[PDB]
Image 1 (tube, rainbow, N blue to C red):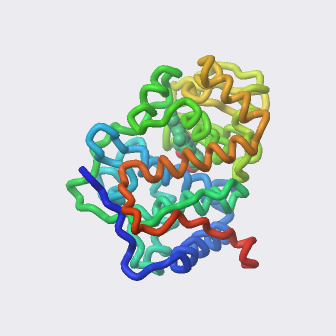
Image 2 (cartoon, rainbow, N blue to C red):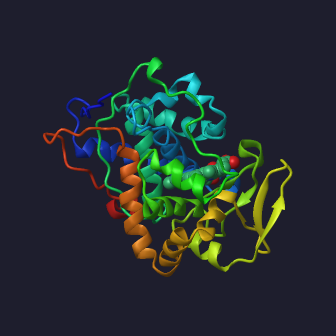
Length: 291
Ligand code: HEM
């Protein structure tokens, strides 16, 4: 497979900045979702799950085709709870019917990180909707009940190295786990709709206790009322991952710079960009525009 990026016919930077502004205004407005966390966290989880199906060996999956819109991927057990993010974006797609599904789903993730005071993420347009038979089969997204060796091996399929894996996992400062979606329950931290290096500081400074939860799954719980998945706690059990966790815990700016690069790479895997194509767009926040 080759997937060539094709700009939506006749659209420029200003068009995409209007879709970003529509998503960001609705993030502001629907602030009550999930006990006042807001939709920002489920939207960056949606952008990672539609990208995370990519396989570097045959170029299948990834964000390009927008195939989450199809039943098979939509109903994947690993995507439980993402229907909420889909439903959020659906009025925005009726307002801007020209944008492709993969461009809308990935842009939702970018808009959410930046509106939650995160780093600017360069974003490229050009994903093209592909047919229902290009939809990847279920089972390509990662399990949470595993160790550092599984994590390393998993992310190799998306050719992410150690630094990129640790930077990307820092998005778990956002939102929370929900028992009915995944068999896990609880937040990773206190400031869960502000993008900060809090995940790393919690992993290094809390007194974590291994416990079983109500779904019979294990998770690491702290006195503070926070939790960590087996795969998160893996990052301090592996010596290579632990030196990077310490780095980001001591330097949020380095975490932001590395997260920015790794998240753009994740959203663009599998896509070939012609050099006639526009450079990556840097969108302004509502705040920068006075809106
Ligand atoms: C080995 C890797 C990963 C595993 C096993 C994993 C697993 C999970 C699980 C089990 C949840 C809870 C779902 C729920 O009950 O609602 C979750 C939530 C979330 N994940 Fe991850 N994750 C991984 C990587 C990532 C990455 C790479 C990102 C983003 C760059 C990410 C972003 C999120 C976000 C923001 C949420 C919160 C969503 C919400 O609050 O509804 N995760 N993750």
